[PDB]
Length: 317
Image 1 (cartoon, helix red, strand yellow):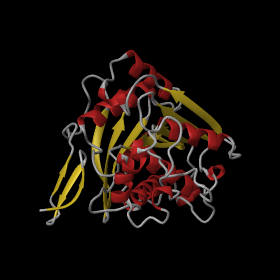
Image 2 (image 1 turned 60 degrees about the vertical axis):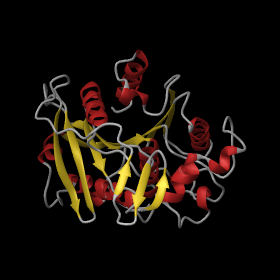
Image 3 (image 1 turned 180 degrees about the horizontal axis):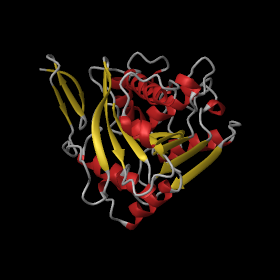
Image 4 (image 1 turned 90 degrees about the vertical axis):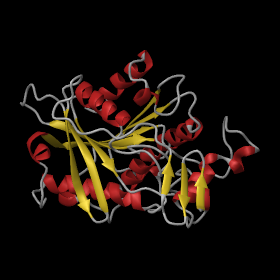
């Protein structure tokens, strides 16, 4: 019997058995991906609360220099998708090889059982875990990080809800009484169609249906206790009295948008607010074209997807 529902994404029963939308099944890590040459391993970042990940290492054809790290958070409205899906595996294989970087695909906790800020906390745990490698305080070090990772080139990002998550990580890092082990800094933020919303319809957003929007339902499930509801700074970063976007804790920031994404105008407002917030870094915007959310993961062979991957490659640098 049904306790919660946010169709088409998720159904939760009295017993805590959950039906989720599943856009692709999980695939296994690979010693060497046939198409891209990227190696992957599944590792435990933390046992409790349980946080795992897949790490991606491109072909090591030269080893003069160490590689940028890209910590990636999948989308799925905080309640579906996976760090290990066919789509994410194949996508990060492409990115890792094209950009020549190490990728970390984070399997953070999801609704219904873990409301925000659980996912936020898991991302922070991930970053601490990475930074403890750099100052030699990691109890169970990943050799790939010790051997191939350039810790001065840490990038953090994702799609939609995952990009929202990265954004909140940036704010935490830019907070004064917050530090990573060894006071490690984040180089860059990559936010691809980030999930942001608000109580008032803006731009091309439908006016009357706004109260019934899927975003309202998703936010209520992810964080019902949130003060201000859909206007809480976690979901609406441009809301009055939110932390200033001048405190984003990186030095380069690329915001990615698309034509058919429901978050287009929110994303556009967000970038523009960062621009006039006083933030000091390299701020960039990329309009990926007439596409949906995350189109490049689904159709990586299109000219538009290839153009996006190329653009990202020149950013993750």
